[PDB]
Length: 189
Length: 189
Length: 189
Ligand SMILES: CCCCCCCCCCCCCC(=O)O[C@@H](CO)COC(=O)CCCCCCCCCCCCBr
Ligand SMILES: CCCCCCCCCCCCCC(=O)O[C@@H](CO)COC(=O)CCCCCCCCCCCCBr
Ligand SMILES: CCCCCCCCCCCCCC(=O)O[C@@H](CO)COC(=O)CCCCCCCCCCCCBr
Ligand SMILES: CCCCCCCCO[C@@H]1O[C@H](CO)[C@@H](O)[C@H](O)[C@H]1O
Ligand SMILES: CCCCCCCCO[C@@H]1O[C@H](CO)[C@@H](O)[C@H](O)[C@H]1O
Ligand SMILES: CCCCCCCCO[C@@H]1O[C@H](CO)[C@@H](O)[C@H](O)[C@H]1O
Ligand SMILES: CCCCCCCCCC
Ligand SMILES: CCCCCCCCCC
Ligand SMILES: CCCCCCCCCC
Ligand SMILES: CCCCCCCCCC
Ligand SMILES: CCCCCCCCCC
Ligand SMILES: CCCCCCCCCC
Ligand SMILES: CCCCCCCCCC
Ligand SMILES: CCCCCCCCCC
Ligand SMILES: CCCCCCCCCC
Ligand SMILES: CCCCCCCCCC
Ligand SMILES: CCCCCCCCCC
Ligand SMILES: CCCCCCCCCC
Ligand SMILES: CCCCCCCCCC
Ligand SMILES: CCCCCCCCCC
Ligand SMILES: CCCCCCCCCC
Image (cartoon, rainbow over all chains, first blue to last red; front, side, top):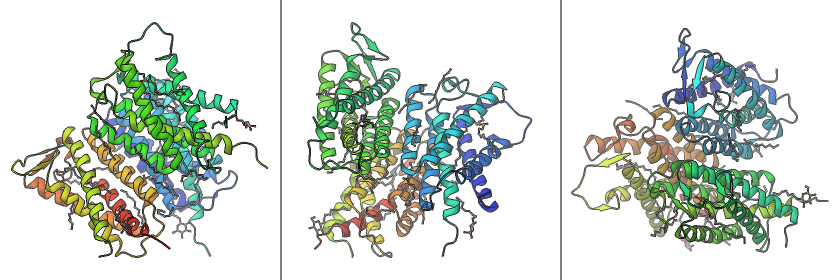
């Protein structure tokens, strides 16, 4: 792998912590409800939820490093900005989930687009597309399995929120950037 | 004209589509209600609404190209970012229209200002001023004519929402940028 | 002092006006209620509130100029952008104050972080930390004294809103930038 172990671990933990904050926001606003109770929870989430997102974070960062021309100019400042953007957008979906689907989804698309405009490149966008498909698909399957459910005003995409698509896209863009940063910030001559 | 026909057509369509999304958001949140019913509607809007905004988009882009020193460094990335900002702000007004007028209007002014800070120049700002006057004036006239109405908590500017002023301003700034892009993206040596 | 008197006065007034807008937003949304009535009010605020914030604005700008390496490239465009960001974030706290504390506080942290990412440096961040401690501490004392109170869904930090911490932080970052601008914009050869 191109990531060092320690790097993948930090990325995993960063993904996990951000996921717990965002998922807690969804639960406490009634954006989503879990139905699973036999599993251990971490905060408001089943233990495997932060593992999945943390794994996805390190995985997408790794993936970027196998795509052409990882950018060596990427900075901690840019990375902090992208994480903030993704977290900000995530918690915003909790706050507006009960509003009509068009302005809500459009708002999140706007945030995702601006995030890419400021920070993303072609391969970054590609990583975003990959998770923008896989993320919602996994959630649809879990909802279909009765593991959790979305609020009725927030379930238009086969039982899950349409905002998940631009939300995951922005996530993929930033995770890619994070992988670029992991290399770029290594000690230099 | 400085725009090519094909360019003006794309700008017109971009304006029209964004307008339909934003106007639908206003209707479905109860920000506005139409009273006209004898005209054909496109989605939630009278057919002439997207024509007006699309026309205004191409027109403002054209106008910029007659103002001093159109910037040749303008990119698709910048343009996508500005459109996202304008659409994001537009749908946000639908979401917050029922809140008190001061924080709502201030929020939209903030978005408009930041949009200009990131993307606009002097002539861009001038295009913004032009539509920030004309836009709301046209709406005031239409409301006065009983064509549509704003929500009572959102009609303080002679029957229309005070947020229309910074919203149109941001629109004018980005449309100007779009005209700069139309020239800048032409095939080069 | 490094600031000229006229500069400190403009900064003071800018701070005062922005504070009045933000504080009015808090009062009118029920984010906060004043209990003091024997003092003259300016708009929705006791007269000393805008004095305190204006004083804090000029003071933090001054403070930055005693910290290492004030940036001479700082522009009016950057400064307008930062003020807009701080005001936008301020009024947003009024709009979302009744929502659950985690997504609300996280949203404001995100705005503060992005603001620093775009505009701040090390000493700027330090100014932010200084007021992110002092601001909320002063408010806690005033609330303890019964001078005003926060909404029950917005008082988790010893009686004041946890969002005050990232809000003041962003304020400190931008005020620092404003002090840099005051020097940088002086007439040049
Ligand atoms: C090969 C590595 C493992 C691959 C696994 C790829 C799939 C990962 C994602 C889909 C999974 C999560 C399914 C899920 O349970 O989420 C649901 C449960 O109800 C949580 O409910 C929700 O409403 C929240 C949707 C989560 C949105 C995730 C966005 C990621 C942002 C956090 C990272 C920020 C750091 Br750049
Ligand atoms: C010479 C070219 C023709 C000039 C025409 C100039 C005037 C254009 C604008 C004012 C017109 C629209 C009047 C109108 O009907 O709007 C109302 C109807 O109730 C729609 O109601 C609303 O609450 C929405 C206000 C519309 C805000 C428009 C912002 C433009 C953003 C979309 C473009 C984004 C791409 Br950069
Ligand atoms: C040495 C110079 C004087 C130092 C004084 C330092 C302390 C300043 C700040 C803490 C003071 C204000 C205490 C206060 O009364 O505020 C309360 C009263 O209830 C107002 O209530 C609220 O809910 C609003 C909290 C105010 C948030 C202030 C953020 C500043 C943004 C405005 C400036 C933007 C320009 Br960069
Ligand atoms: C992208 C966010 C991850 C950044 C932190 C990764 C931590 C592991 O990264 C390690 O950091 C060490 C200390 O700087 C360096 O000496 C190593 O070269 C580097 O591999
Ligand atoms: C600003 C958004 C408009 C961009 C798309 C304009 C489409 C018409 O633009 C045309 O694009 C062609 C294909 O690239 C070029 O060959 C032409 O030079 C150009 O006029
Ligand atoms: C950071 C916001 C403050 C900017 C305005 C400060 C006004 C006082 O600033 C003064 O401006 C004069 C006119 O430009 C200059 O001639 C002086 O050199 C300058 O001190
Ligand atoms: C070059 C400075 C970049 C700052 C990052 C800001 C992130 C914004 C994401 C929406
Ligand atoms: C720029 C905004 C485009 C996204 C709007 C899509 C609406 C989703 C309908 C389900
Ligand atoms: C290569 C250019 C990719 C741009 C994608 C940004 C759009 C995201 C919207 C959800
Ligand atoms: C400031 C260092 C350059 C690295 C670029 C990363 C994001 C830019 C997107 C155009
Ligand atoms: C960009 C979001 C995509 C939304 C698609 C909705 C599909 C609905 C099928 C029932
Ligand atoms: C140089 C990169 C510019 C990115 C555009 C972002 C648009 C933000 C508008 C508020
Ligand atoms: C920077 C914010 C300035 C705009 C606030 C104006 C309030 C409108 C009152 C009708
Ligand atoms: C020439 C400078 C113009 C700056 C204008 C930006 C402010 C818009 C606020 C609604
Ligand atoms: C990156 C290409 C330069 C074009 C500038 C357009 C917006 C900048 C506003 C200062
Ligand atoms: C920036 C928004 C301007 C608002 C003006 C309000 C005028 C009210 C007249 C009845
Ligand atoms: C170099 C152009 C900087 C534009 C300032 C934007 C401010 C955003 C603060 C969140
Ligand atoms: C990036 C977001 C981190 C901030 C969340 C903190 C929550 C506050 C709980 C009182
Ligand atoms: C020296 C780097 C400082 C970065 C601080 C930005 C984080 C603010 C979050 C509330
Ligand atoms: C464009 C002039 C340079 C001044 C920099 C101020 C903010 C930058 C933060 C990295
Ligand atoms: C970043 C915000 C900090 C919040 C701290 C909450 C402390 C609660 C003590 C009762």
